[PDB]
Every structure is written in C-alpha cells, then in structure tokens.
Image (cartoon, rainbow, N blue to C red):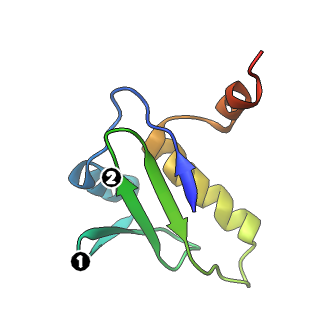
Amino acid sequence: MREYPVKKGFPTDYDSIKRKISELGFDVKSEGDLIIASIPGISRIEIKPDKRKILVNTGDYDSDADKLAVVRTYNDFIEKLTGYSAKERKKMMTKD
C-alpha cells in the first residue's frame, strides 16, 4: 500500500475528494464504507482519507499499459489530492 502525506488545508473528506476527483475528470464509486477512485490506466483503487494523512492501495495494473506510465497518472492524481510533490520526498531523505 502507498501512504501519502496531507497538506495543511487541503481536502481530506470523502465528499471533498469525490468532488476533486470529478473536478479533475475522474469518477468515484462507493463500495460499502470505502471509497473507490476511477482513474485511467488503473482498474480500481481504494482511498482512505484521514485528518492525519491519506493512503492508497492499488491492485492489478494493465500489463499492456506501462505500469510506469500509469504510475505517472496515478501519482499525479494523489499528488494533486495531497499537494506534496515528488521533489518534497527529498525533504524526507534529507534529515540533516
């Protein structure tokens, strides 16, 4: 599973994200109490927003589609859903 941080202010609510998803041009499915995101290249993904942070869980990807490519679209999705950038990751690696 993938765990992403949350920006101070950014949306962290199912509905909020639901709008952000559809606002980006994506779809969202309600499977029980869990939220499902609808992105291109990916079959189905689970989203669990929390006041603290958020996390995503991917299943199987289209072997026909560059898993690395779909990743660029999958990350970008969360990237905007979180705000943090890959460049930010450095902050993590850079302790000193």
Quadrant in the picture for the N terminus: bottom right
According to the picture, the residue beneath numbered tag 1 turns out to be: 32
Amino acid of disc 2: Glu
Residue situated in front as seen by the camera: 2 or 67: 2
Please tell me whether mark 1 sits on a helix, a strand or a loop. Answer: loop
41 to 56, vertically: above or below: below
Q: What's the residue at 23%, 77% (across, down)?
A: 32
- Give coordinates of residue 88: x percent, y percent: 65, 30
Q: Reply above or below: 59 against 86.
A: below
Q: Nearer the viewer, residue 43 or 96?
A: 96
Q: Secondary structure at mark 2?
A: helix
Quarter occupied by residue 58 = bottom right
Q: Amino acid at mark 1?
A: Gly
Q: Which residue is mark 2?
A: 23
Label pair 1/2, CB-CB below 8 angstroms: no
Q: Residue at x 47, y 54 (%)?
A: 55
Residue at the image position 75 percent from the left and 64 percent from the top: 68
